[PDB]
Amino acid sequence: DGQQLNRLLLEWIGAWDPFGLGKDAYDVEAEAVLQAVYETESAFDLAMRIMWIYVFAFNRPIPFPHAQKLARRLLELKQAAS
Amino acid sequence: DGQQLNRLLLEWIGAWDPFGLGKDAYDVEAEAVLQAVYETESAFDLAMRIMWIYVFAFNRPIPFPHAQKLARRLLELKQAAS
Amino acid sequence: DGQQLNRLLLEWIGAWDPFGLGKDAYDVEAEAVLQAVYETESAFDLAMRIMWIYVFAFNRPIPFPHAQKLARRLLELKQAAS
Amino acid sequence: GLFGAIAGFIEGGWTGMIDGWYGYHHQNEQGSGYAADQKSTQNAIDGITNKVNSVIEKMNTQFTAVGKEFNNLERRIENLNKKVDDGFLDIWTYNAELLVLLENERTLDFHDSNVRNLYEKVKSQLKNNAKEIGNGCFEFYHKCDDACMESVRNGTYDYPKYSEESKLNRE
Amino acid sequence: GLFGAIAGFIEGGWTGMIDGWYGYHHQNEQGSGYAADQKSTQNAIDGITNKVNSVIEKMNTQFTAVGKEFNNLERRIENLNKKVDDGFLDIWTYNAELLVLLENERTLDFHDSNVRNLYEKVKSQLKNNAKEIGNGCFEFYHKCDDACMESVRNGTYDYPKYSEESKLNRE
Amino acid sequence: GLFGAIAGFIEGGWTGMIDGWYGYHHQNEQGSGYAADQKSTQNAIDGITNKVNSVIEKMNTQFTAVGKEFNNLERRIENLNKKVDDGFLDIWTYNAELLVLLENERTLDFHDSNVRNLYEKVKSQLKNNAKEIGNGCFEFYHKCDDACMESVRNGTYDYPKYSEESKLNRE
Amino acid sequence: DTICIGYHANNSTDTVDTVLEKNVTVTHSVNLLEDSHNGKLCKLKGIAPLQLGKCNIAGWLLGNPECDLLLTASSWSYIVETSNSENGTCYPGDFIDYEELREQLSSVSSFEKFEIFPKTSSWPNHETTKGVTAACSYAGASSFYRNLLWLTKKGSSYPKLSKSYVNNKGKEVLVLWGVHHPPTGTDQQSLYQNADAYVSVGSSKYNRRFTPEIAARPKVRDQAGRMNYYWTLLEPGDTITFEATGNLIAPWYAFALNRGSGSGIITSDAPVHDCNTKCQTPHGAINSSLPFQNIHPVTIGECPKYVRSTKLRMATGLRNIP
Amino acid sequence: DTICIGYHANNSTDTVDTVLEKNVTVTHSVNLLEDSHNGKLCKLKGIAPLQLGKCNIAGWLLGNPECDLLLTASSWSYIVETSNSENGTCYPGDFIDYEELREQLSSVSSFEKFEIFPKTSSWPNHETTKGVTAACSYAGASSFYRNLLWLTKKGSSYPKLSKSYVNNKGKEVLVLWGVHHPPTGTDQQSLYQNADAYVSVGSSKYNRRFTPEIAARPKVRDQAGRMNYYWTLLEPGDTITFEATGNLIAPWYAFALNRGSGSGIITSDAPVHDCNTKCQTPHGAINSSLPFQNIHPVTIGECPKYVRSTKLRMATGLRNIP
Amino acid sequence: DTICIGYHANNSTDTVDTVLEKNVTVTHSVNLLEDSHNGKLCKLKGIAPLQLGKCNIAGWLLGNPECDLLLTASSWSYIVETSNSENGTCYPGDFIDYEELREQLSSVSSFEKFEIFPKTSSWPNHETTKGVTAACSYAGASSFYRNLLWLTKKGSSYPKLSKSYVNNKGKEVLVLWGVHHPPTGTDQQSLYQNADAYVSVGSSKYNRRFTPEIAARPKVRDQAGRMNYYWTLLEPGDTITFEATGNLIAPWYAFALNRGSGSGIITSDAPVHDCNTKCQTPHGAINSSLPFQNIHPVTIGECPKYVRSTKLRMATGLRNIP
Ligand SMILES: *[C@@H]1O[C@H](CO)[C@@H](O[C@@H]2O[C@H](CO)[C@@H](O[C@@H]3O[C@H](CO)[C@@H](O)[C@H](O[C@H]4O[C@H](CO)[C@@H](O)[C@H](O)[C@@H]4O)[C@@H]3O)[C@H](O)[C@H]2NC(C)=O)[C@H](O)[C@H]1NC(C)=O
Ligand SMILES: *[C@@H]1O[C@H](CO)[C@@H](O[C@@H]2O[C@H](CO)[C@@H](O[C@@H]3O[C@H](CO)[C@@H](O)[C@H](O[C@H]4O[C@H](CO)[C@@H](O)[C@H](O)[C@@H]4O)[C@@H]3O)[C@H](O)[C@H]2NC(C)=O)[C@H](O)[C@H]1NC(C)=O
Ligand SMILES: *[C@@H]1O[C@H](CO)[C@@H](O[C@@H]2O[C@H](CO)[C@@H](O[C@@H]3O[C@H](CO)[C@@H](O)[C@H](O[C@H]4O[C@H](CO)[C@@H](O)[C@H](O)[C@@H]4O)[C@@H]3O)[C@H](O)[C@H]2NC(C)=O)[C@H](O)[C@H]1NC(C)=O
Ligand SMILES: *[C@@H]1O[C@H](CO)[C@@H](O)[C@H](O)[C@H]1NC(C)=O
Ligand SMILES: *[C@@H]1O[C@H](CO)[C@@H](O)[C@H](O)[C@H]1NC(C)=O
Ligand SMILES: *[C@@H]1O[C@H](CO)[C@@H](O)[C@H](O)[C@H]1NC(C)=O
């Protein structure tokens, strides 16, 4: 179910830690990424959302391929539980 | 003569009514179009003046071909009386 | 030596007088051109410095080829004394 | 200048073509003449009008703004007032002069682009049925009467039809 | 529109290509499919993100700004205050609406440019080993199995290898 | 990057060509060497200087601006003053950093454009008297001594003269 | 046979500036900068402006005798002061919070003057007829402001007066009055009898008490004395109360104010004419839909943005190459 | 066999405007304009705002009896006035330099109220218990401000008082007091005995002397008298000295102020709720990283730039052409 | 045989930012941002600035005895206060409209001080020599301001004085004076004899009357008394009249002012040096033709636009690719 899937996806997003701030510094941005996850099936669209999410919050560009890697894990995982 | 030609050209310009404002809402713009008419023989130059005249006054773009149609009638008419 | 080379290069820069202001109106700009001279061996780089020097000081664009002519004399002269 | 067409590989304009911004000069056995491209022109105009409206409508017509008076013991507020007025004025003057400068560059380049795209539009339609002179001109390797011309302007020129005929003459 | 590619000589997009902004459609004897170009796409994205960050970071988040109150004998200073507030607001609104407008033009044109450069990238690699249809398509004058395709996408296509084979079929 | 030439189909610059921004590398039987194109360069420079002057001259040198003092009961006007100063400063800083950013993009693209137009200038002059390698290079199908070279740079290369000679070798 | 691509050119001489080059000739363009005006002062919304002429706002509202033309004035689209608006306070003194008053007025589009305290019936115990001065002559006779009433001693006494007004006009009322400060104690006695006189004025918002400051100052318009002028906006339903034992120049007429927006005071020496415009400046009116103007930073109505530029022409057509 | 170049398209309906055309559909874009808020008033830095309710700043600091809820208040993230903040000065008069005081307060994040002059021990020679008024009723009884003490005559005498306070709190102290102006001489006598009374207050920075202005004014809340309210910021180490022979409404409680930045006074009728935000406006909080907002020009905290725009969407992807 | 097209590259390390990428290496560029200054304070138009040192504007113009170096000063390009400008009013009191006075001075480029009322001949009926105080010591002796004259009673009387000055200097004249407020009635008597003293000052524009406010205040520099300082700009042809029966600290020297533009007051602890510049800031001078500077928002002269930026480099050449 989502309750468990939601907690895990969130743990991971924090752990991604692109700016060396610790897993707990990204709680706001992580929810935005979670939300975005349930809105699409295309790794590319999602990769785009994430990068944007993190650019507004932090004023810093995440390498595209790095973002693209995170999205693939998350959509694989969404489908894997669904 | 101009006195009669001037009154008719003006009636028409108001009647064009591109914005559904009534023939009387365009009196200022109509004079500007009349003036512009005596300044050229090229339908294209005139079509350009009109559209500009109406864009400044109303902040709204008139379809080019619609404007272009009005200019053709007016230059045909100018030559027809001259 | 530089003492004599410095005085001559400066006299000339003032005499260039691109804006019809008299040789003495360019004393500040002339030093900047002299300084720039000891910083390069490429007539083209130097031609670029001069034009920039004079554009900031006077808000006026010097013909490139005219500037380019001055630079050639100066680098020829720098090498000629060195 | 950016696209190499206007004042580039097409060195000059046609004081003679009065019905449009971009167009064609055609010469066959049946007669010459000039013809503007409505679509190219129509597109450029809707574009430029929009560029201009956006600039005008962004400008608040200026509603009443009048001076304030201050007494001889209100010199600081008086100067503050003046600092405000002049500062906004330096800015509106600056944005405006600069905006027009930048936009003029873009407008002219826009035209260069429209022309080039028109040339290459035609070039891709004809292919080997003609050669490029290099001055905005194509020479046909076959007879192209006025009917054929019209197809070319309005986009429907048929290559296969003349590909054979053109293949013979060319080689 | 500036570079003639998007909504130009390549009339339409591929609702079917979901892994990138620009890419290829290939058909040989061995099968079809769609493939995005990571390098073209990767470059465009780093570019657009930077365009957007520069715009956002230039914007001071607005720290506390609250109204001032003035008494009924402070009407001039009260109006001066209001003149200040509104003037800055006309400006930030104006720069912002106008900036986005201008930048949107540039962004879209940026994409047109990326596509065109990709087309001509491929065109210069293949040369006479294929013909240009004129709609973003090339027809091969030789069999190009999936191995050959990959070389083309990632930039390493070998012309000499097939130049002979291609020379026979073509003529 | 927009025009595909600089850091595109011409992958690299010539640390070796010191007399200009754009130019030629020539190799014939009679010797090599590097040669800048004055016209291309001359045009680019007048252009860039003008871009820069317009930016500088629009900037009012700042004449005397000093602080005002306010007493401990003039805290509102004191804050109004500060709001004015900072607001103009956010703006001048913002326009300036942003202007340079945008203009730098345009300047670099301007250069890309100049180079591309130079390549295609040469390409249209030579035609079939040479082949395009695809890296800013043309290979001649005939002997082109230094005299011939000069004609090419300064625009007067004669095609018909060598069209026959070139036609034999090529096929 | 051949076909060519080409672009329009004409005999247009219009030039525009671009960032890469100046003075570029184009085939079509639009001017965005209005730089012409008609040199007259005009109506707005068909209402003529109020021309004050030789009077200024102070002179107008007090009714300086030099301002009788203004007596009949009631609505205007804006107010015009000239280089010769010198008739203000003809009796020397300070007009308190004068700049603020002008600001109030910059948003008043009309008013109805009325007789707040009728001269003939309000003041049965005081002298109302000796309050004239050579400082405010009119037709060579000592005279006085038309909107104020100078009260003095009757016989040899000035009893304490107390007079109130209730605002039932349904809008703000502008009330003006003065406080007189003789130059000597003996002069004080001649006019008001009482050495220890005061003036107290109160409403819900205004509340002030004044006492005479008797001292020699340099003579101005022959007068070593001074008079201070005060004003207040009496809100609807509010009451104003004057109390004095001397030195009061009492209100006679006051003004019920009608507020508008887009009104203002301008200073101009340009002639008022009967034309009508949407945008007025101190040099003359502008009849324009252009977004910019370089005519004047001061405007009444709906105007183009003022900028210092001398030229803003935006190319619309292309580089003109015949 | 064939190979084609192409570009992505999808079922995206997002449109953006460009300078050459409006309402263009693109494949991806970002909104730069936050236009939504949560309609509540929230904490900042986890500190709740001070909701003044029916009182205003004046009513709060004086301790208008209608404001007892505010008596316990000491820290806040910002201050909220509503459309009904009408309880201020319940005894009619002017609160001097009130707007400046509000400005001072816009940068005070907390304070400690304290008893500057304890009612029970500071004033052994004066009456402290008859200083109530029907103008400040509370529970239908004459009452008075909680932060001030109205001193009156004891028996039939008001001796000269002199009372000083030294600031040892280590920070600025806000001291408030009043000066009373009876409407008649006989009333003056009833309350303070002395006709020629004065109040003098001095510290290193403030130095003023007041005298009673006795006169009839219209009644306000039944009162023909008036009371003026004054305040000062007593700097660290400074002393304030009050001297009077009548008419003094003495300080009772004062405020040691803790300064902060990013505080402010807003006016809003939106409900305060227990949520927490980084950016607060008078319509509701914003939880956003967008650079712009069109919600409100008044903000507390860290906010997007306010602009009048209704739409700012920047294309990121390309023209969408399925 | 072959021919190639190509573009210049060099060993340039200059980088610039563009909207699509940061830190791009180019072949040529120009810096538009001056970020260096010479750390000294210099002449402008070859005129040295006025360094006030330990005095401030008030201390200077009154002639605080601590300011004797400034006695000879007459022209300056701008005025410099430091972190130690603490010598102002040495006798405690308020300097009225002080901030405005500084503003006036920010546009005065020079002046001629002169003896408006010569000590030795203007005041034949009053004491001029006992008006010193331990509050203004100088060399350990009671002393006083050099530009003011403290008048006191002669024997046991202070008769009414009346003294006027006519401005024939052809320009505005700055006149300063004071009003003294003893702390006790008995002290009042010791100095001026008269309990009911006043000071009245008048010209065409200024008109004020002052009376002594006698009361105990905390001692400042040993003094429980206070002195207020006043100033006015006497217009050309105007007269100023002082009248008093006590408590007047009369003008001794005054200043005929020469106006300029581009002058100002700055605060800086940077050393004044003999160099010459076109643009001066509080950190040091700038000798630059660059359009921008990030050194300081406060400038005197002709300066680059101040911006917060750390880098503004505009590419001129192309992407550098060796
Ligand atoms: C309406 O405004 C007009 C001007 O716009 C104003 O007219 C002026 O009246 C004054 C006041 O009397 C005139 O001033 C006099 O001029 C004569 C000669 O020029 C002088 O001799 C007078 O000064 C003498 O007396 C002074 C006082 O003692 C001395 O100080 C001085 O040295 C002289 O001895 C005095 O200056 C002025 O000339 C006219 N101006 C014109 C052009 O009419 C009129 O008063 C205003 N009316 C009202 C009632 O508001
Ligand atoms: C706290 O604020 C509340 C309101 O927010 C405030 O309540 C008000 O009290 C006043 C003062 O007494 C009330 O005003 C009266 O209303 C009655 C009837 O409506 C009138 O009759 C009264 O006026 C009469 O007397 C006046 C004086 O002579 C005359 O001028 C007038 O013509 C009448 O004869 C008077 O206007 C008011 O109605 C209430 N409002 C409400 C809703 O409660 C309260 O006083 C404040 N408390 C404190 C102590 O700060
Ligand atoms: C020019 O400026 C200089 C400083 O820039 C200024 O020098 C100061 O003089 C004052 C005034 O007398 C000095 O203040 C005293 O310092 C001593 C010891 O530090 C204290 O004992 C004194 O205070 C006592 O008395 C006070 C009054 O009753 C009490 O309140 C207090 O508690 C003490 O009992 C007093 O504070 C000050 O130290 C010097 N500073 C320096 C560094 O010289 C000089 O006065 C100015 N000159 C003029 C004439 O403008
Ligand atoms: C523009 O050039 C024209 C002639 O073509 C000339 O009349 C005009 O003076 C020029 N303007 C400037 C300022 O260069
Ligand atoms: C944009 O076009 C869409 C349909 O494609 C339409 O719904 C919308 O109203 C248009 N907006 C405007 C204001 O032109
Ligand atoms: C720019 O890159 C250079 C090396 O090429 C490096 O020294 C510098 O730190 C970079 N700057 C930033 C802030 O990226």
Image (spheres, coloured by chain):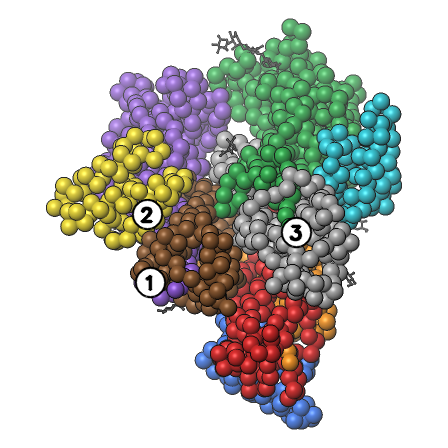
Chain colours: A cyan, B yellow, C blue, D brown, F red, G purple, H green, I orange
Q: What element carries label 1?
A: loop
Q: In which quarter of the image is residue H234?
A: top right
Q: What residue type is labelled 2?
A: Ala
Whole-Å distance between the Cαs marked 1 and 3?
39 Å
Q: Which chain carries label 3?
A: H
CB atoms of marks 1 and 3 within 8 Å: no
Whole-Å distance between the Cαs marked 2 and 1?
34 Å
Labels 2 and 1 within one chain: no
Q: Observer-nearest residue: G232 or I174? A: G232
Residue to which mark 3 is pinned: H2
Q: Observer-nearest residue: G187 or B4? A: B4
User: x%, y% of residue I274?
Assistant: 65, 74
Is residue I106 visible from the viewing direction of this image?
yes
User: x%, y% of residue D51?
Assistant: 47, 47
Q: Measuring 36% from the left and 19% from the top, which residue is drawn there? A: G169
CB atoms of marks 2 and 1 within 8 Å: no
Q: Measuring 54% from the left and 74% from the top, which residue is drawn there? A: F126
Residue, far top: H140
Estimate how packed mark 3 is, as few (under 14), some (14 to 19) or many (20 or more) residues with alpha carbons within 10 Å.
Answer: many
User: x%, y% of residue D38?
Assistant: 39, 49
Q: Does the residue labelled 3 lie within 8 Å of ligand 5?
A: no
Residue to which mark 2 is pinned: B47
Q: Which amino acid does label 3 sit on?
A: Thr
Q: Mark 1 lies on which chain?
A: D
Q: Measuring 35% from the left and 55% from the top, which residue is drawn there? A: D146
Residue D29 bears which disc, if any? Answer: 1
